[PDB]
Image: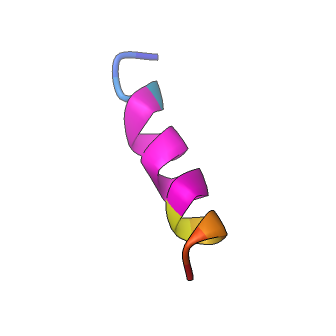
Amino acid sequence: TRQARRNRARRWRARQR
C-alpha cells in the first residue's frame, strides 16, 4: 500500500513500453 504508487508507475511503464 505504501508503495502502491510504485506499482502504478509500473503500470504506466506497462503503458509506456
Q: Where 15 falls versus 4 (above or below)?
A: below
Which residue shows up at 46% across the image and 17% down it? Answer: 1
Magenta span contains residue 10: yes
Q: Nearer the viewer, residue 5 or 1?
A: 5
Question: In screen coordinates, is 3 left or right of 8?
Answer: left
Q: Residue furthest top?
A: 1
Residue at the front extreme?
16
Residue 8 picture location, percent across and down: 52, 41
Left or right side of 4 for 14: right
Identify the residue at horizontal 50%, vertical 43% (top origin).
7
The magenta-colored residue range is 5-12
Q: Quadrant of residue 6?
A: top left
Tell me: residue 14, above or below residue 3: below
Which quarter of the figure is the C terminus placed in? Answer: bottom right
Count the labels in the image. Answer: 0
Secondary structure mainly formed by the magenta segment: helix
The one of 3 and 17 positioned closer to us in this rendering: 17
**Residue 9 belongs to the span the image colors magenta:** yes
Q: Is residue 9 above or below residue 5?
A: below
Tell me which residue sits at (60%, 54%) in the image.
11
- What sort of colour scheme is used for the picture? rainbow
The x and y percentages for residue 5 are 41, 31
